[PDB]
Each structure stands twice: as C-alpha cells, then as structure tokens.
C-alpha cells in the first residue's frame, strides 16, 4: 500500500535498469564506460586503470556521439554529427585520435557524411564508405585508396546495403567484411536500378514552406528486387598509381537462373571465405566455400565443397540461413540446422563431405552458437525445464558429444532463467547477462574451470526503490490445444485476487518465429497498466511462433493472417475460462505485424473483444517489403499465391468493425510499414460506414520513438484503454 | 412534440429543397429540366413545349453528365466521362447532336480528355482546350483549327487557368472569352515554369500497390508566381493552310515593372475589349480599354483611356477588382467601387474622362450589378431595413438617380429578405430567387411594368413534411462594440425557453469579407444540433467581415489572425451575458479559414471554450496560396510583413491547448489547404505534450465531400460534440 508504477514513471523513466556493457579487447582485458571515463579492466583480478578520461575531449568543440578503438589500442575513432537514416544506417563525421602522440590526426581525414566506417580486426587499417564507394586507409594519417568508382546515390551501393538488405537480410548497414588478419576486404555491391521507389511527404520544421518528398528504392512484395555482386580486394597490394583490382566471386549457377540474395558472409581462414546464397523463393539455399588461388589471384569456389540446404515445410532458417562457425584450421564448421523431427540443432560439417552430423537432439531448439574452442563448443538453448521462453548457456565436449554441461541453469534458478553471453577474445572468460525473471544480473566467469569470478552488476540500487512501489507480477504458463502446449504470459496487478473479474488487454505480435511469452524482466507500458489500472496484460505464442520446432513455426507457411490470428482469439477465450477475467472487457493491441493481427482479430467479428489499438499495422501483404513478405507468402502471382494475398487483407474485414471500438495510429514518415497501409484501412472503414479513432504522427517513422512522440502516443493509448474499460 | 430533425435526416437527405434552375435562351423563352425532359417555357403565357426527351438518348451507350445547347438552338453539346480536377476544373468527352437532322456528328469529333468547351455566344462556333492548347470549330462537323502550339502539361496553359488562377482569381477553369457576336476569341496564357510544386501522396483503390505522388504547380505565399499573357484571335479569318494569328495585348507598362495578375476581362462592344490588371501587392490596379484597329489588324489600348484604381486602407475590391458593365455603345460603363466613406457603391464612368460619378450612396453596400437597359440599371443591395445580411433587387432610373425602386423588398417581407435574380436576354423578364428566411420561393416577373407573372416554385411539398418535425428557429440580431453594430445569428432549438442554460456551439468562418450572419434558410448540421441535441449554433460577423464597408472589412489588413479572432472570443462572452447559455459548455468549430480561427481561438487560453473542431485549417500563412494570402498579408519578407507572418501561426499557441479538448480533421489529398498545415499543428501539439483528437481522410480533398466521407466526418464530429457537452 505505497505508490504504484504510474504512466509518468514509465514515460519519464524514473525507475532505471543498470547495464554492464563491456567491449572485450584481448583474452584478458575489456573496456567499460564509467562516469564517462573509459576504463580497462583486468578480467582475472578485477583491478582497473583509467584508459581515457571525460577530460581528454573537453575542448573537442563537437558533441561526441560514439567512440571506437583500433584493435591494436594505438588509435581511437570519434563519431560525431550523427544523423540517423533507417533502423541501422546513419551518417556521421569522424576524427582519429593518436593515443601514443596524444593528438588528433589533422590531414587526410575522413570525409563529412561518411556512411560506414570500420577498423580491420587487427592493427589499425581503416575502411569507410562515402557517396556509395569504398575507401581504405592503411595508416590513419595517410591518403586513402579508392576501391569502387561506380557508387551512385539510390542506384549503386558499394560496401553498404540498400533499404531491404539493411532491414531484412543483414540487419546492418555495413556490407563489407575484413579477413581475420586484415589482408582482404570483401564487400557486396547492390544494383537498385529498377527497384521502384516508395514516396511520401516529410514536413520538417514549420519554417519549411513546401513539404519534402522522400523517395526510397523499396521493393514491395513481388516487385523488382535489387541484384547483388560480391568482391574481394587485397589491401596489401594497393597502389596509389593504379585503381584497385577488385575480384568478383559470382553466385552459384543454381542461384543465377532467377532472382536470389546473398544472405551470409563469414570468413573461415586467412585465405578461405564462406558465402550463403538464397533463392527469391526462400526455401532453397546454397553455401559456397572459396579459397584464395596463389597462381591466379582470384577465388576458387570448389563446387565439391558446396552444401545445399532446403525445406519442404517452409522457408530456410528462422529468418535466414544460420551462420557457420569454423574450426581454427577451417576444414570443418558447426551450424544450426533444423533436424527431421523439425527441431533446430547444431550440425557438424566437413568442408567436402556432403552430409553432416547432429551433435545435439531433443524437444527443444538451440538459440545460437556462442563460442568455439579446440575442444569445447558453447551455445544458448531453451532446453532447461523444457520451457521455450527460457534461455541458458550450455557447453559441449567436442571429443565427446554426451558430455553436455549447463553453465547457467543452476547459478540462481529463482531469479535467472534468461541468459545471454559475451566471451573474451579466446574464450578464457565470459560475461553472463541474466535478464529475467528477476532484476538483471551481470557476472564474470573464467572458462578454464567455469569458476564464477565476481558480480559485475546486480541492480540492488533499483531493487531498493522498487519495494517502495506496488509492482505487478508475471505468470508464465501454457495451455493445451490438440495435445501440444502453447505458452502465455500475464502481467498481473499487485495483490492479484484470483476471485475477481479483471479487465484484460491482449498484447500481440504473433509474427513468424516470434515469442511474446518469455521470462524477461520488463519495465514498460504493461507494467503501468497492471500496476496502476489493474489490467491483466497477457500475451500468447500461438501457431507460427518460434523456438518450438517447425511443426509450430511453419504452420502458417504461405498462409499468413490465418492460424496465428485464430489462435490469438482462441487464447482470449481460454482466458475467460480461467474465471478471473471480465468477459465484457477484453481488449487487444499490437504494433507492426502485431497491428495487423490486432486488426485481423477485430475484423473477424468473433465478438470476444470490446476494442483494440493498431500501431503501424500491415494491412495487406502486397504493401510490405518483398524479402519478409515472400519468405512466408511466396509471390503474389496467379501461378503462385495471389489468391491468399487477396484473401488476407484487413480491408475486406471492414464491415465487422461495426462491433468494436478501434484506434488506428501510424507515423507519416514510416519508411518500413508505409503510412499507405493505415491509409487503406481508414478508407475501407469510411466506405462501409464504421466509426473509429485515429492518430497520425507527423514525421515519425516506424519507431514512433522520438521523445515527445513516444510520450504522446502511450498517453493517447492509455486514455483510449481506460475509457474502453470504464476505468476513471 | 413529433419527431426531430435527426443526424440521419441531414446525412441521408430526407428533407429536400426544390429549386427552379432555368437557363434563358431568348428574351421570351427559357429552358427547364423536368423528370429529365428539357422543356422550353414561354415567359409571357407560361405554356411549354417539350424541347427534348429523356428518351432521345436512351441508347446513347454512355451515362450523360451534362448538356449545353448552341445559342442558335440548332445543336446540343453532350458531356460525359466527367472526371473532376480542382474546384471548377475537370475533363470530359463530348458529342454534338444535330437537332435539325436528329443525329450525332460522327466525324471530326471533340477529343477525349477535353479540358474546356464553350459555344460562341451566338450561332454555333465552338472553342475547346485539349492538352493545354486552344482549338476552334466553325461548324460542328468540320475540322477544327489549332490556335496555340505551346501548351505543355503543368507548364504552359493556353485557354485554361493554372491552379491559383482557377481558385483565387477567375473562380473558373475557363480562360477564354468570345466577343459578343463571336468574331473574336480572346484568351489568357499562363507560364508556370518556375512555380514550385506541392507534392502529396494519393492512395487510390487498394489494388494500387505503390502510392501515387500528385504534384501540382502551386505558389505558396511569397513564392514564385505564374506569369500571364493575353491574346485575341479572329475566328473569321482562319486558314487551314496557315497557323492562325493571335494578336497579343501587353499589360500596362505600370504593371510590367514587377509581378502582376490579369484579373478581369470583359467585352464592351464587337470591337472593344476591357482588361483589368492587378499588381502582386494587390492595392493598385489598372483598367485598359482596347479597340480593334482595322488598319493594323491589332488592338489599341490608348493610355488615355486607362483607369487606375487603388486603396490606402487595404486591397482593391472585395476579393478582386469589380467587373464593369458597359452601355450598348460601349462609351461608358458602371462599376462597383468603394466610396470615400468606405462603402461599396455603383460608379459611372466615361471611357476617356478620368473621374466617375457615384449613382448611389448610403450606409450600405451594393452587392452586384445585375442588368443594364437603355434607361434602367438593376442591382442587388443590402440597403433594405439596414441589415447587411439581407439582400434585395433594386432598379435605378438612368435619366434620374433619385428614382430608385425596390423591386423585391415588399413582395413578402415576412418570408423573403434574401434575393438573387436571373434576367432574360434583354431584361424583358426576370426570375427572383428568395432563399430566406422562409422556404425558398421562385417567381417570374416582366420588367416593362414590374408585374409579378406567376409563382414558379414555393416548396409547399416540403412545407407539409416540415410541420411534422420540431424544427429550430433562427434569430438574426446584433450587438454593439465601440458604437458600431456587429451581427450574430443563432439556430435555436424548438420550444426555445429563454430561462434555461443551453450549451452553445460557435460556428465560425471569419475570413476577410465573409458573412456568416445572414437571412438564408439552411438545412444543415446545425439544424440537427439545434433540433435533436438542443445546442444553440451561433455565428458572429466581426471585424474583417464584408458588406458593412471598409472600416469593418479592412480592419484586419496586414494583420490576419488578430481582430477577427479576438472579436470571435468577445462574441462568445456576450452570449454568456445573454443568460440562456451554459457557461461551462461553449464550443467552437469551423472549416478552412474557419478552422484557422477556431484553432487560434482555442490556442489563446481565454478559457471561454471547453472544446473545438478544426476541419482543414490553415495553420500558418506561409503555407496557403499567394494570391489569397498576400492580398491580406503582403509578402513574407523582412522589408514587408514577415514579422506578422511569424507572429500569427497556430503552432506557437500550442501550449495553451492544454486547457481544451481539440479535434483536428484533414483530407490527405487536399490540394487547397495542404495536409501539411494540420501535420504541422499535430507535431506542435505532440512536442509540447498536449493530448487531442485527430482524423485524416484518405484521398479526400478540401471538400471532404465524397458521399461516404461526408457522412463519416459529420458523424465523428457529432460524437465529439455530444461527449464534450455530456449529451446522450
Ligand atoms: C591489475 O593488476 C595487475 C597486478 O596485480 C596482481 O598481480 C598478480 C600476479 C596477482 O599476484 C594478484 O594478486 C595481483 O593483485 C597488473 O598486472 C601487471 O601487468 C603489467 C605487466 O604487463 C605491470 O603493470 C605489472 O607489473 C603487472 N603485475 C604483476 C605482479 O605481474 C595489471 O596491469 C593491472 N591491470 C589494470 C590495467 O588495471
Ligand atoms: C566538415 O564540415 C565542417 C563544418 O561545415 C567543415 O568545417 C570548417 O573547416 C574549416 C577548417 O579549415 C574552416 O573553414 C571552418 O572554420 C570550419 N567550420 C567549423 C564550424 O568548424 C570541415 O572542414 C569539414 N571537414 C572535413 C573533414 O572536410
Ligand atoms: C595475414 O594473412 C595473409 C593471407 O594469408 C598473409 O599473406 C600471405 O603472406 C605469405 C608470406 O608469409 C605469402 O605466402 C602470401 O603470398 C601472402 N598472401 C598474399 C599475397 O596476400 C599474411 O602473412 C598474414 N599476416 C600479415 C601480413 O599481417
Ligand atoms: C460581328 O461584328 C463584326 C465587327 O464588329 C462584323 O464584321 C466586321 O465589321 C464590318 C461589317 O461586316 C466589316 O467592315 C469588317 O470586315 C468585319 N471584320 C472582320 C474581318 O471580321 C460582323 O458583321 C458582325 N457579325 C455579326 C454576327 O453580326
Ligand atoms: C500598397 O500597400 C503598401 C504596403 O502597405 C503601401 O506601401 C507602404 O506605405 C508607405 C508609402 O509607400 C511607406 O512609408 C511604407 O514603407 C510602405 N510599405 C511597403 C512595404 O510598401 C503602398 O502605398 C500601397 N500602394 C502601392 C502599391 O503603391
Ligand atoms: C405558347 O403559346 C403561344 C400562343 O399564344 C397565345 O397563347 C394563349 C395561351 C394566350 O395566352 C394568348 O394570349 C396567346 O396569344 C404560342 O405562340 C407559343 O409559341 C407557345 N410556346 C410554346 C413553347 O409552346
Ligand atoms: C580509375 O577509374 C576511374 C573511373 O573508371 C578513372 O576515371 C580513373 O582515371 C582511373 N584511374 C587510373 C589511375 O587509371
Ligand atoms: C519451395 O516452395 C514452393 C511453394 O510451396 C514450391 O513451389 C517448391 O516446391 C519449393 N521448392 C523446393 C526446392 O523446396
Ligand atoms: C421522362 O419524363 C417524363 C416527364 O413527364 C416522365 O413521365 C417519364 O417517366 C420520365 N423518365 C424519367 C427518367 O424521369
Ligand atoms: C475516345 O475513347 C474511346 C475509348 O477509348 C474510343 O472508343 C473513342 O472512339 C475515342 N474517340 C474520340 C471521341 O476521340
Ligand atoms: C504551325 O505551328 C507549329 C509550331 O510552331 C509548327 O510546327 C507547324 O509546322 C506550323 N504549321 C502550320 C500548319 O503552319
Ligand atoms: C569525469 O571526470 C573525472 C575524471 O577522473 C571523473 O573522476 C568524474 O567522476 C567525472 N567528473 C565529474 C565530477 O563530473
Ligand atoms: C487443432 O489445431 C488447432 C490448434 O493447434 C485447433 O484450434 C484446431 O481447431 C484444430 N485443427 C485445425 C486447425 O483444423
Ligand atoms: C474597441 O474595439 C475593440 C472591440 O472589442 C476593442 O478591443 C478595443 O479596445 C476598443 N477600442 C480601441 C481604442 O481600440
């Protein structure tokens, strides 16, 4: 009976989680920002010298957005004038500071408006992208060599991804890859010549008299995609009297007979590079393994060494083919592939032998491979307790596959069931991040004996303040439909009394391979809704969700907008059954795919929901980008899946919105889910004569993430939900 | 105590006003459509033959949008495939039907996509515009002659106006003018080369995968305007072996020294044409009077016959310089100009004498000159009863200026105080349209003796149905501020009991020279609000309004967004004083300028209003079009009026919205008041953390006038108002 977690608490960020972001630099040391002084810590003993002080750049003259230290400690890269583009891309200006000579490098600098910069993985070589071309600097103070000359704004991209490659395939702006010791620089080249443009108004400061039209090469579903090429250049034989020789590695022939994507590049040795390609119909992929050829000076990709990967029940990978991890000599590698029972497990490959050996099996999936030593492989899985929403670090003995030790399950089972890990340069040490269900807990460990060295952060600061407030609780459980379990989670109000009728808000994402029912600790809008408004905020992972094998995941293949929406409605019904839910007060809300599902649900006239909110929803699949959409729906042609594209829009369900209160919200400068989508919904609802609520956000994009917009939307949503539930 | 006027009554249009739209064809006959048979009526005796039957075109094969009969009765022009553009512009396809030969003209037809068509004023010559060029047809079946070759989409306009000329100067798409007997075709040419474009998304049917970007030459305030040229061509000497000759008529030299507009063209004789020009700073204008010069084949405007008109207190004209009406010999003309007491009266000019003589004076304005015979001039004025919102037909004896007869005041003073008139080809007859405060009443009259011939329509059909419903009443009165009267109107609920506290909705337009307090009979949203919801819907004409002379009209010169908004707030206060108003329930709403004022008012934090709705508001003047904006504000430069442009935005008042409930509504395809404006408001409110309501209308323009959008918005607004007033 103290204060509750209020809307303002969330919005103003009064209760803050501490983190412990460290960047390893050797096998023995790491860096950490402390009161703006980057410090170097000794993994073993824990002592720390100051590496650089908040002082050093008092009079830089510019506000410093980020730093990045050369792998050999000698120089430090300074990032300023940060201007965001899409989710990962941005441009900045850069300056290099010599640490020996305590000075800034004044001549032959990095241009203003640089799109990407990266060090070589050892030493202090530099590669950067400027007006879509790649440049290399051997020494920070020396003149840079030009690698490509073809770069052209919104047409040719060298070393950086276009829109759809950034967002849907690499999850990165960067499209260049150094070889381990820095000899080679590989890069992708993207030709967007015939990719159609999305165009939308941007309004800017009210001083701007005419609105700007932003235009972006963006392939909607079934439209014309970019084409890609791959090159490797030798930075050691750069001339300054000759243009650099870039060596192309063509796609596999099987890929060349139609549209495809380059979807993974991973160096294997100093002279071996592995590449993964994927057909536009994303159920067939091929891996190439290429060796440097001394006498030719090109890259030989032995077809004997190819490895085909495909799926009959859906698409390849969770979102794309998994990345390989090679052994030091690079003759074999481990990779997560789905077994024949449909479960994602670690497989073991020989460069030239065509099959592989699973080194794990079970009714659970490997989340990712984390580290590879000479006789141990470390990975994260959801095996422990057989709960998919959990997350734990395991290690397996390379010389004996039965010897599997769980490195985190036992460490604190009550507080910690969701871990991630960050290893040191050779895995002498590792840092565990526990993120639920208790308050996050960062610790350090040495791999040699798996000894827990010390506690890095434990959020006891926050723990104090939090017993001062009536927090909500989280139940993670499952229900059974057709004797398979489907997990749900519920944020329950403080003093939850199971005999009363609570109003319930269904929190939905439901996208392919999504997981909204997990054991993470979160301070968010739902916390406020439970704590202050006594609303149960529930999420449910139905068909289509991940981490439970392909029978659940691929269940929506080619059939988006069906099973995942019906299972959501079902879950609602089940919650009524549970008894502590007010029947006549169930709501639903979600963002992106979440908004689509919300809308599809509200549109189905199942009468289960009183109302919902869709934020930046997809409304019909022909509008979303090709790489994502087609991965699940294939092509919107009559020979393929046009029928289901058309059978699955929100607008056809417009009529049924007559039975629900609806809130449509969408940022006008949304480059991802275009405003178009919401605009099509409103139109549909107007036409069939349905009242609803609406909200645009001028110049906000898909994040609606700008400070004041963020507060404004949640505020507007809160009022909506309260009035919908008749709370005061 | 029967049924009331409901929201559905308004939206579904259950109670319909009958009209009597007649198109005169001679001095003795007129046409009238009647369950789809155009009939010719005999003005004198009232009998009627059928002129053409709904039958004639049963199997035309196309749906017929409109007709237009050649002045000489021989042919009939048929308009189909109507596709709307802006307020007046559209394109259509056309067919000419021979009435003698009872046939359609099959060869040498009018192209699909014709932008404007018009007959010569006598005979059956044709002029049309296609891809921005002018063509003339001497006979309907003959090949057309090409007049201009320079026409170019969105750049060069021959014979039609660009955006801003259509909307703000000619109130017409058409920019060509026949001489009285059809000898000459005058036309304007518009060069939009450097006029910047407004661009906005259009979404179309949901089948359209990528949104279309509409782009339109549109000069915002202070931006680069179009330039204009004026030509006359002789249609009688057209060749078919020679490109046809267009004599240009340059603007006044005094105009060529800076930006200007052509703002009126009016033929005076068979060989005399009058032109009015206006400087971009719209307080100085010049009239040219041009004669055909047989000897040069050219047009001569003696500088000695020019007539300079200007204003020191504001701009010239109500919205532009008034049109001249010439005597038959074309040596003198009448024109409405403002006198030195500031009142708009009819002035009498001699082509070459530099002064003019007022033929009316008084504390009232002439609304317009209607007809001119050899010894009588007919006009509409707001003189009767000294009420500006009234409207009556007067006639003045040309031979004696003291002999002024009021032709309509007395006809039915109780039912009729707002008249318009339509004269026959020589003013032998005239049709009065009474439009308030009673139900509209159309009658016919002969001018010879001013005898009322018969009643054409009296809406008794509607009168019947209307006593079956509890209608509201309208009070028209004034209040006094600084011993001048300012008029208000109130739509009062049925059984209005002056001792109760009613909730009040302030209906605002407030634009320069506007009039929202008049005696017209209207069936609209306000009727519903009064009748069914017992809300007083009030309007108030404050400073800036028209028809009361320049001291009231010009009061907001260079100072938009001040006096007109403060007077609106004042009026609200006055209504509280009246005693029958609920203090804590005053609302305000308006559209366009009306939305601007509403917003400015809500933003002033006068605490008088609980809430308001802005539909397609102007938010800052730099966004609206040049011709309108500058007419009142001048140029947004530091040497001129930049300061007041900046001191008068809605967004700077954002903070004060914290004290009111707000609804922002705007059509996304608004080519007039661009969506941009509302987008800037929302952004401002978000940034300062103010909650509000919003609604966009996908693909609707400034009218929000499409059938389903129209119903949807008024519905959405109604809920808003009801909840704001706590009404069931
Ligand atoms: C952190 O301190 C260590 C030294 O402190 C530890 O030495 C161990 C041998 C052990 O006995 C332990 O109890 C003790 O606390 C620093 O190691 C140093 O490294 C460099 C040589 O490269 C030198 O500066 C020191 O001479 C050397 N110490 C020893 C005794 O070997 C280490 O530098 C420091 N780390 C930082 C950056 O804070
Ligand atoms: C990047 O842009 C900046 C800012 O526009 C440039 O800054 C100017 O640099 C020169 C130094 O000789 C001076 O003329 C000015 O004093 C600078 N302006 C400021 C505010 O510092 C800069 O030159 C550009 N840098 C690079 C790497 O080209
Ligand atoms: C980094 O790896 C590269 C690639 O193997 C090494 O470069 C080779 O060096 C040896 C000489 O010791 C030669 O056999 C090859 O000709 C080199 N490859 C070429 C042509 O690039 C290099 O030794 C490694 N280390 C460095 C130089 O940092
Ligand atoms: C319309 O008026 C025009 C001129 O106002 C008349 O034609 C001109 O005037 C006289 C009379 O025919 C001639 O001397 C000229 O040759 C004519 N000008 C030209 C070349 O067009 C014409 O008579 C009138 N037509 C009608 C319908 O009455
Ligand atoms: C049109 O209006 C302008 C602006 O109101 C008038 O010019 C102002 O008046 C006097 C005399 O020119 C000056 O002291 C001001 O500096 C003027 N202001 C500006 C910005 O022009 C002008 O008199 C009017 N008539 C015209 C076009 O001659
Ligand atoms: C209408 O009638 C005209 C006939 O003239 C006589 O009409 C009688 C009704 C009567 O009033 C007499 O005074 C008139 O002299 C005829 O000539 C017109 O052409 C007719 N018009 C039409 C369109 O039918
Ligand atoms: C390198 O390539 C560019 C473009 O092809 C060319 O203009 C430039 O001259 C070349 N430089 C040398 C050294 O040949
Ligand atoms: C990929 O999936 C599509 C759609 O079901 C189908 O046409 C094809 O058989 C699949 N191809 C392969 C190689 O699995
Ligand atoms: C054609 O007009 C006459 C009016 O007298 C009417 O009787 C007939 O039914 C009409 N048809 C239409 C379409 O109104
Ligand atoms: C105009 O359009 C229709 C449809 O394309 C065509 O059949 C017709 O003949 C066209 N001709 C004209 C009127 O120029
Ligand atoms: C008339 O004008 C146009 C454009 O200047 C020219 O191309 C055409 O050849 C001319 N022809 C005639 C018919 O005189
Ligand atoms: C950053 O500067 C100093 C340098 O050592 C650091 O100790 C301190 O905590 C920070 N300075 C302050 C007091 O803000
Ligand atoms: C069993 O599967 C789902 C849940 O997985 C269930 O709701 C459905 O009714 C059954 N089968 C189907 C989808 O035909
Ligand atoms: C009279 O005009 C307005 C009308 O309310 C008022 O604001 C003003 O104070 C009065 N007088 C003067 C001197 O402006």
Image (cartoon, coloured by chain):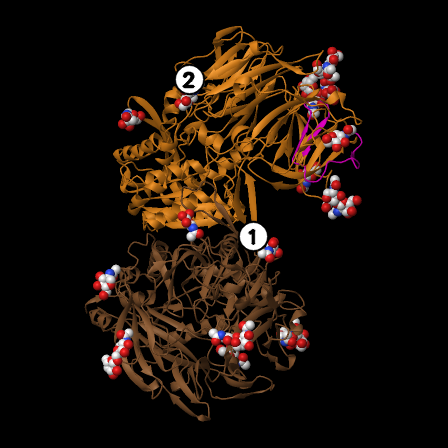
Chain colours: A orange, B brown
Residue at 67% x, 15% y is A270
Residue B253, position as x, y percentages in the image: 67, 73
Numbered range of the magenta stretch: A100-129
Front-most of residues A445 and B562: B562
Give residue A183's position: percent from left, percent from top: 71, 19
SS at mark 2 in the image: loop
- Chain where mark 2 sits: A
Q: Residues within 10 Å of mark 1 (few under 14, many from 20)?
A: many
Residue A605 higher or lower than B192, as above or below: above
Between the residue at mark 1 and the residue at mark 2, the CA separation in whole angstroms equals 51 Å
Position of the C terminus of chain B, as image quadrant, is bottom left
Q: Would residue B87 appear left or right of B104 to someone viewing this image?
A: right
Estimate how packed mark 2 is, as few (under 14), some (14 to 19) or many (20 or more) residues with alpha carbons within 10 Å.
Answer: many
| Chain designation of label 1 | A
Q: Is residue A425 above or below residue B398?
A: above
User: Which label was assigned to residue A211?
Assistant: 1
Which is nearer the N-term, disc 1 or disc 2?
1
- Dot 2 corresponds to which residue? A343
Looking at the picture, how far across and down is residue A259, in whole percent?
52, 26
């Amino acid at each position: 009976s103290r204060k509750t977690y209020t809307l303002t608490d969330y919005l103003k960020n009064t209760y803050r989680l501490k983190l412990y972001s460290l960047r390893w630099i050797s096998d023995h040391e790491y860096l950490y920002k402390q009161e703006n002084n980057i410090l170097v810590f000794n993994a073993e003993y824990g002592n720390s010298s100051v590496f650089l002080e908040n002082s050093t750049f008092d009079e830089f003259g510019h506000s410093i957005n980020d730093y990045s230290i050369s792998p050999d400690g000698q120089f430090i890269l300074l990032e300023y004038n940060y201007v965001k583009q899409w989710r990962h891309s941005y441009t900045a200006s850069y300056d290099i500071y010599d640490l020996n000579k305590r000075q800034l490098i004044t001549e032959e600098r990095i241009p203003n408006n640089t799109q990407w910069v990266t060090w070589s993985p050892v030493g202090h070589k530099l590669a950067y992208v400027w007006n879509n071309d790649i440049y290399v600097k051997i020494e920070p103070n020396l003149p840079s060599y030009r690698i490509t000359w073809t770069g052209k704004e919104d047409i040719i991209y060298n070393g950086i991804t276009d829109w759809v490659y950034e967002e849907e395939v690499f999850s990165a702006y960067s499209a260049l890859w150094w070889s381990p010791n820095g000899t080679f620089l590989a890069y992708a080249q993207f030709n967007d010549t015939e990719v159609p443009l999305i165009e939308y108004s941007f309004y800017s400061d009210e001083s701007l008299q005419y609105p700007k039209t932003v235009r972006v090469p963006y392939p909607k579903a079934g439209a014309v995609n970019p084409t890609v090429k791959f090159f490797v250049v030798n930075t050691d034989s750069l001339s300054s009297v000759t243009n650099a020789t870039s060596i192309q590695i063509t796609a596999p022939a099987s890929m060349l007979i139609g549209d495809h994507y380059l979807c993974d590049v991973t160096w294997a040795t100093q002279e071996r590079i592995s590449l993964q390609w994927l057909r536009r119909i994303q159920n067939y992929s091929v891996m190439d393994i290429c060796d440097y050829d001394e006498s030719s000076g090109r890259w030989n990709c032995l077809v004997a060494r190819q490895h085909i990967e495909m799926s009959t029940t859906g698409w390849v990978g969770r979102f794309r083919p998994s990345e390989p991890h090679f052994t030091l000599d690079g003759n074999s590698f481990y990779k997560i592939i789905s077994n024949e029972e449909g479960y994602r497990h670690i497989c073991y490959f020989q460069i030239d032998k065509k099959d592989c050996t699973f080194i794990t099996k079970g009714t659970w999936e490997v989340i990712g491979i984390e580290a590879l030593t000479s006789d141990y492989l470390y990975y994260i899985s959801n095996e422990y307790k057989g709960m998919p929403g959990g997350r734990n670090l395991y290690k397996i003995q390379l010389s004996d596959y039965t010897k599997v030790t769980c490195l985190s399950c036992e460490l604190n089972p009550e507080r910690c069931q969701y871990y991630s890990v960050s290893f040191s340069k050779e895995a002498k040490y590792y840092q565990l991040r526990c993120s639920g269900p208790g308050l996050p807990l960062y610790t350090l460990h040495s791999s040699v004996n798996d000894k827990g060295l010390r506690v890095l952060e434990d959020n006891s600061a926050l723990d104090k303040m939090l017993q001062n407030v009536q927090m909500p609780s989280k139940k993670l459980d499952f229900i059974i439909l057709n004797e398979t379990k489907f997990w749900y989670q519920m944020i329950l109000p403080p003093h939850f009394d199971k005999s009363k009728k609570y109003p319930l808000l269904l929190d939905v994402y439901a996208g392919p391979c999504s997981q909204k029912a997990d054991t993470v600790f979160r301070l968010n809008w739902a916390t406020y809704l439970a704590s202050t408004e006594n609303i149960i905020v529930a999420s449910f992972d139905g068909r289509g969700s991940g981490y439970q094998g392909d029978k659940i995941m691929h269940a929506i293949n080619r059939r988006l907008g069906t099973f995942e929406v019906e299972d959501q409605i079902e879950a609602a019904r089940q919650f009524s059954k549970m008894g502590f839910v007010d029947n006549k007060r169930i709501a639903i809300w979600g963002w992106s795919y979440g908004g689509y599902v919300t809308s599809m649900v509200l549109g189905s006239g199942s009468g289960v929901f009183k109302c919902g909110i869709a934020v930046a929803p997809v409304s019909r699949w022909e509008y979303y980008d090709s790489v994502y959409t087609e991965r699940y729906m294939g092509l919107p042609t009559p020979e393929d899946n046009l029928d289901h594209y058309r059978n699955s829009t929100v607008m056809s369900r417009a009529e049924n919105f007559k039975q629900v209160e609806y809130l449509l919200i969408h940022g006008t400068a949304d480059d991802n889910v275009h405003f178009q989508q919401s605009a099509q919904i409103s139109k549909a609802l107007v036409d069939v004569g349905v009242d609803f609520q609406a909200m645009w956000y001028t110049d906000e994009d898909h994040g609606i993430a700008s400070s004041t917009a963020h507060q404004h939307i949640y505020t507007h949503m809160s009022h909506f939900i309260k009035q919908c539930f008749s709370l005061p």
